[PDB]
Amino acid sequence: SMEFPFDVDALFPERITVLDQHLRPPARRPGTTTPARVDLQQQIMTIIDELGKASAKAQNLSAPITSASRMQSNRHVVYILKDSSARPAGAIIGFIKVGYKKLFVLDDREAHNEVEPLCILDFYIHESVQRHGHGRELFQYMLQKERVEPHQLAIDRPSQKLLKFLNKHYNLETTVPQVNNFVIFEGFFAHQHEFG
Ligand SMILES: CC(=O)SCCNC(=O)CCNC(=O)[C@H](O)C(C)(C)COP(=O)(O)OP(=O)(O)OC[C@H]1O[C@@H](n2cnc3c(N)ncnc32)[C@H](O)[C@@H]1OP(=O)(O)O
Ligand SMILES: [Cl-]
Ligand SMILES: [Cl-]
Ligand SMILES: [Cl-]
């Protein structure tokens, strides 16, 4: 999939790496690798920049919606999928980016609600390996770490591929019409209904 000069496996030991505005390299014990020629955080910044550009090309966007500089100035969390057993040994498969956002969301009565749901903001799997289950790997990992259910999410400008994905995997089919270009599904307001 996506190839980089520096040692990705040394940088990201785990299959899925979780980063936020700090862009902090995963933990490592002193001595377990020689200090790289490129600082670890610079490697991370380059990876985020390139992933965001690739996602923008996939989505036919004139500018990336994910980048190192945007990560540093926002409250977003990115989950990055890498294959530790890739061949030939070196690569990054893709990522999902989420964040809580304050939104004014319409309910099924067309009334406005001030809410702060977890939002799906950017999501990309390299073209060569789309439709192989990697998107679901990332999505599931994120749901588990964030402790949220699919119907509780808002989606920023979902693509056709993502709408199909959400219906297939999570039975998210029926939307509640919005004016803010986010999409929500039936069940979005269930928690508000129960708890207030
Ligand atoms: C808020 C946002 O991020 S909107 C932008 C979402 N990102 C994009 O559209 C970028 C291009 N697409 C991708 O990167 C990926 O296809 C993702 C992230 C949408 C999904 O990840 P994938 O690894 O492809 O999904 P995964 O293999 O886990 O699940 C497959 C399902 O996704 C949907 N899907 C994936 N590719 C396609 C496709 N080319 N056409 C129609 N549906 C598709 C289908 O529901 C499919 O199931 P099916 O094969 O039985 O029809
Ligand atoms: Cl694509
Ligand atoms: Cl970002
Ligand atoms: Cl609802």
Image: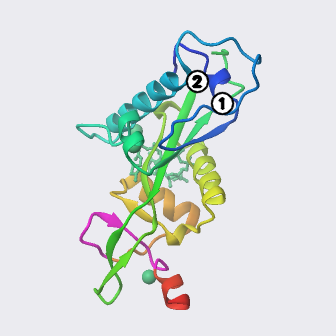
Q: Position of residue 108 (x, y in %)?
A: 35, 86
Whole-angstrom CA distance, mark 2 to mark 1, is 7 Å
Q: Is residue 181 highlighted in magenta? A: yes
In terms of depth relative to the viewer, which is nearer, 135 or 45? 45
Per the rendering, the mark at residue 91 is: 2
Ligand 1 within 8 Å of the CB at mark 1: no
Tell whether label 1 touches label 2 (CB within 8 Å). yes
Per the rendering, the mark at residue 83 is: 1
In terms of depth relative to the viewer, which is nearer, 60 or 180? 180
SS at mark 1 in the image: loop
Going from N to C along the chain, the mark reached first, 2 or 1, is 1
Q: Identify the image quadrant of residue 150.
A: bottom right
Q: Position of residue 145 (x, y in %)?
A: 65, 56
* Pointer 1 local density, CA inside 10 Å: few below 14, some 14–19, many at least 20: some
Residue at 64% x, 40% y is: 16
* Pointer 2 local density, CA inside 10 Å: few below 14, some 14–19, many at least 20: many
Q: Which residues are magenta?
A: 177-188
Q: Identify the image quadrant of residue 64.
A: top left
Per the rendering, the mark at residue 5 is: none
